[PDB]
Amino acid sequence: LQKAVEITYNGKTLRGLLHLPDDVKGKVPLVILFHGFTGNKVESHFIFVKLSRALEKVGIGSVRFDFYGSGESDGDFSELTFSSELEDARQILKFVKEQPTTDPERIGLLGLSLGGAIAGIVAREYKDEIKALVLWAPAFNLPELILNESVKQYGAILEQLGFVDIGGHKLSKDFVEDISKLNIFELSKGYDKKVLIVHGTNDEAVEYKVSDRILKEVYGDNATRVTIENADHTFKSLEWEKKAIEESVEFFKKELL
Amino acid sequence: LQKAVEITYNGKTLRGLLHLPDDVKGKVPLVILFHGFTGNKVESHFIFVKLSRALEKVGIGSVRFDFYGSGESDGDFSELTFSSELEDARQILKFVKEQPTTDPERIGLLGLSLGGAIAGIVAREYKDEIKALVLWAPAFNLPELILNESVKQYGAILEQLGFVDIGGHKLSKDFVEDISKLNIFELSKGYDKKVLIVHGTNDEAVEYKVSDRILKEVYGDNATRVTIENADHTFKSLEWEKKAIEESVEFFKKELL
Image 1: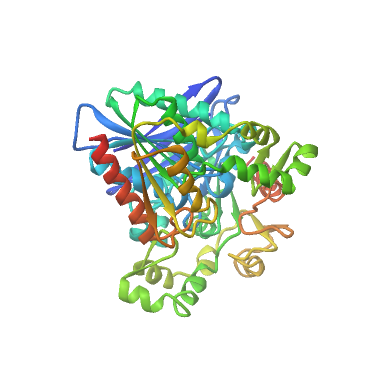
Image 2 (image 1 turned 120 degrees about the vertical axis):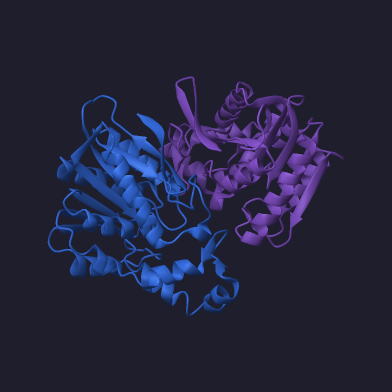
């Protein structure tokens, strides 16, 4: 079952999609998916919708929302910041628990790159409430990346212009300053339930070595990594995409149930 | 205002968004927006939402649906054909006509790339029903590209596997045979109302010189072409984005109203 949902907090309205398995009723496990930098709820080559529909086939619900300033939700990219989506994420988890079909003891999280950073942080905020977590190409090094991409380049423009054109989006200078005082590695530490990392070897957005850091620094032996050899950032292949979703569904099927 | 909508025909469910102007009330001009190959209703860097929300400021509503097998709508890319999305387009136009806020006389059409080819065909299909037509980098030569792409590498793969991986999607073999019998130039010929063409000088998906072909072989005095100097396919820049959306809404508001 697929139908669109709406969230409104403050003066912000969020738009998204909720999935529920048709053949089983009562209270069902749920995974909340967080999208990445400049992405949206469908995500790259529809990998989120695909993963959503694969989950309802194994009796597992899901919700996919558009972060404020991106996609179908309200706002401009300029009034968006990392901590903004952090507030958005909390409202989505709240909304999900307030569903009669939602099982409170079985809730998981999934995030892709920037969404992965948000997912690992929100997982620690609700360490008891989130039973399992999956990180696709987790961009825990987004802070250094933005800072090192703001001094080698864009630095003069951002101050002069107030923003910079990343590619049809207005990257505000507020965004650079807000993520400057955030450390994803130290902010995701403290999650103790099972963790699954999916990373591509030939990832040029978030180099594969980041997952090594996340495995050594952030989580203990409660986190495993599924390495997809030769894959790119978003697993842009029918083969790569299959492995990423299948291992994610298997992982959610075991740890969530 | 923006609300999610749904169309269900022939066992297929289409999901989308309907934009309605808050200021004006009663009956209001609508602009149907068709997205491109491997895209979705939000389109690249959210240009469709931007165009939609910029449209409602003029008091001009719009409807943005995901084609069947794409984005939020049902089905996989494997069951998608050009004629498949032509059928979807007809269903979307019937949907807009059925809405009480909608005014039948002033419906408009917009399409990007393959969506523009869809829009050009549908505009001629309902010549008297569609008041104006806007085309963003219209891929009228899409059948030629796919044909030439198939002989270079797709066809050998498609013959055996039944499909080809075009980057996380399954391109049907029927899709190639389906589009081979199609000539968008002649199919879009015969529209007798005002047409606007927005094309990029540095467009690499759909060459700039095919916009020359459309103005000559497809239309006459009613056709107009805005040239975005040095722009790429989707106007992936805030300066290029402004020119395309600003000029197109002025074309819409003038001839629709």
